[PDB]
Image 1: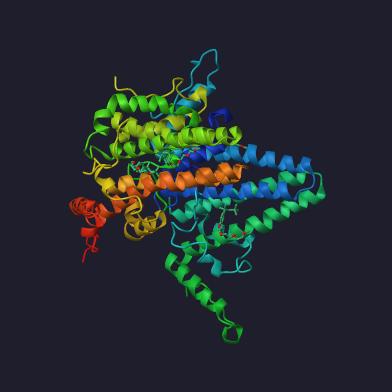
Image 2: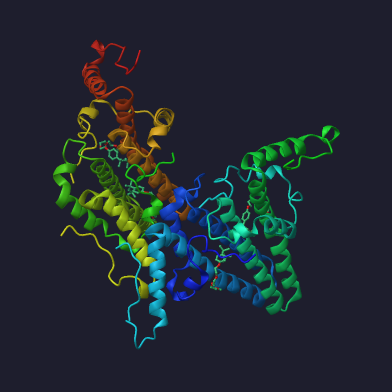
Amino acid sequence: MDIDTYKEFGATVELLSFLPSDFFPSVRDLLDTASALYREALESPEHCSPHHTALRQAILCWGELMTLATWVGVNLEDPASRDLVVSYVNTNMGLKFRQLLWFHISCLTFGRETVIEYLVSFGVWIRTPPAYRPPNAPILSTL
Amino acid sequence: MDIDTYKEFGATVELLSFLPSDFFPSVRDLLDTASALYREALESPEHCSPHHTALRQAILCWGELMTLATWVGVNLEDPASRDLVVSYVNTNMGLKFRQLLWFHISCLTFGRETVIEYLVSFGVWIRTPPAYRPPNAPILSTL
Amino acid sequence: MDIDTYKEFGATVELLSFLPSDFFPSVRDLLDTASALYREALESPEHCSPHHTALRQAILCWGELMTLATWVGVNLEDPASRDLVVSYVNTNMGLKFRQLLWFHISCLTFGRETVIEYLVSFGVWIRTPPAYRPPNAPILSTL
Amino acid sequence: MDIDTYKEFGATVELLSFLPSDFFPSVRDLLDTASALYREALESPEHCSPHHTALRQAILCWGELMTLATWVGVNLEDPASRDLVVSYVNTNMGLKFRQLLWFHISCLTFGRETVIEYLVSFGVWIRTPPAYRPPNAPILSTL
Ligand SMILES: COCCOCCOCCOc1ccc(C(C)(C)CC(C)(C)C)cc1
Ligand SMILES: COCCOCCOCCOc1ccc(C(C)(C)CC(C)(C)C)cc1
Ligand SMILES: COCCOCCOCCOc1ccc(C(C)(C)CC(C)(C)C)cc1
Ligand SMILES: COCCOCCOCCOc1ccc(C(C)(C)CC(C)(C)C)cc1
């Protein structure tokens, strides 16, 4: 159906395509962040925000993927295929999951405008080669 | 996070357990309906509704699962494990995907109130013993 | 019953496990700090603050646990069981005790707002990658 | 440090020594009384009273000591030392726990004035030799 996860929020896969893989914390770290910061709201019966909605749905998807991984580890006889499926799930799907968790948590924290400006500036920085860009990337922080 | 995907909309996993698993249409049929009725609103850059948001996220998760299934069919050589994984994905995960797609499409089309009343009425129907269970099961309609 | 030591102050065990366990100072350091800064108020006959009340109760519980440890050392003869009990007490009970002492001392000193924001920021920091977080760890300061 | 559990409220360990140790009910009975009368206030996120603030901490200390007792029963293999530890806990630390529970539940149910007057009157009654001691001891009541 050609749907973009972030077009509804004012971003675009081509905008977050620049952030590397080493930019996103682990899935456990991002889930702990989401819990400690917005658990009372995600477990709430209210439409608190589209970010909350999408974040709930993504957490449910990841839970079902973990269920799949456990089922595989328990029900597959071939260790090669089992490990291959589990590694695919974790690495590749969690890359997208981390991307989405980061986007939504960071937006809820800072602001849509702030996050999009950070994305533009980080793209400017990461497109520039090292010989002509500063060595320290831009930084989004509450400190 | 103990999150319920229907609590922000007014239902629960216990109110939708009134409906059996063989009740929900196919993922093919539900995606056909979703396209035909809300393609231009799901592809839109707007929080048209929390239902639209959740439905976008669910469709994206299902697309990622289909990608996983194709990747499995390609890479995994063990036919037993390949078929096991594909069948688990489809049957199990698509069961929940059908529940979610049904809930959101039906709500968008008819009303949260109508869908909850339909759930309680279908519970009445399916609990009624067959000797007094009418054959004309409840059904959602606009007419 | 289901009582949380912190939800009357505006925190949570989840929000204090958001920081590492190797972050919290030793029980002796925290007791020295408590003495130095608030001895006259903890020994005072006044509800100076809920923080003072909770800190009094915690210090008394830790004193009773140390009494238990000495009683074990002098009565129990099996060195295995003796050392095992003392180690359990110290490690496990002191983790919680020093989390609580840290929370309450730091609150009395800086502010509930400051301490909660510090928890959030330090967790996000220690979870963020180095190349994209500030390089210096956060720290509370009255200076 | 030298902290008194009761001078913050208007009593002392000496004013409570008028009551014998045989006087205090079981920890089970006092926790039942608490769960009956102030459960929804001890489980609340509010500084309802210093009495609640202290009773929460005491209940948590007791829970941790019960956890220690179970951990000992499991991880120890010298029943002599195991029983020594459990008995010491339940008797020695239980006496203080039930003193504190009595004091707080009473000052919450009746009041500081009533409880202190009761302590003084019971001291009179119990210092009075038996030959001149009425049987109608002072008994806290709202009737
Ligand atoms: C195997 O299923 C048994 C019945 O499960 C019903 C449980 O009720 C909650 C299910 O709700 C959902 C629906 C969809 C989903 C997501 C969005 C994760 C989609 C999926 C199943 C395609 C991964 C998660 C939970
Ligand atoms: C393999 O990594 C590629 C990097 O990402 C490229 C762009 O991907 C777009 C991200 O889109 C999605 C799609 C689905 C999801 C959900 C929420 C369904 C979660 C997932 C990945 C666990 C299935 C998240 C982001
Ligand atoms: C063995 O009993 C001797 C009687 O001693 C009573 C006077 O000592 C002070 C009592 O005050 C208390 C009350 C409670 C406590 C805490 C809160 C630490 C609870 C406990 C006893 C469960 C560890 C500590 C001291
Ligand atoms: C190994 O410990 C794990 C860390 O657990 C952190 C969460 O702890 C939940 C209980 O919290 C507390 C905190 C303090 C306390 C007091 C103050 C009573 C002191 C103690 C730990 C000496 C009993 C009791 C329970």
